[PDB]
Image (cartoon, rainbow, N blue to C red; front, side, top):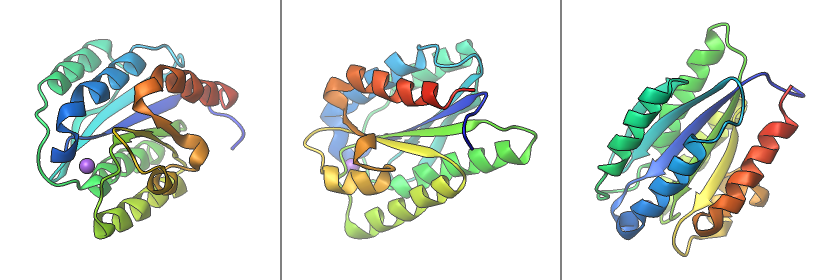
Length: 184
Ligand code: NA
């Protein structure tokens, strides 16, 4: 698959208890990237996870829906366990559905998290992120706090795909460059 005509962005956002003082950083990354142009065929989805993984806004190219979705993200109060594997399950379900319809788009997952996962929860996040990659998704991890980059490199496609959220304006540019390289 050398290039694609359109790109679907999947934000998978950690709203567990360990990221409480950092939700604003997570929101602001998402809000800055959600506003960029990226592609003439840009759709995005907002997925949040803590005790479960929930699709807060289904894939859409409509700016008003995105705007409302950003408003629900401003309301988030972090708390609970860190079930990141369900977050990926939510994106993989939307991905498989879209390719099942006559839709050939690239899938880009952006997972924002502190990486603070017990071994079992990490074990199944890695498996579900590998499940997304078989679905053709490219996975980036945007690390929050003093994130463990060795763990995130296993969730993301590589160490190349792990960026700190604190300098993520540079990371946005880096993520968007990879989209452009793969843009027919
Ligand atoms: Na966490």
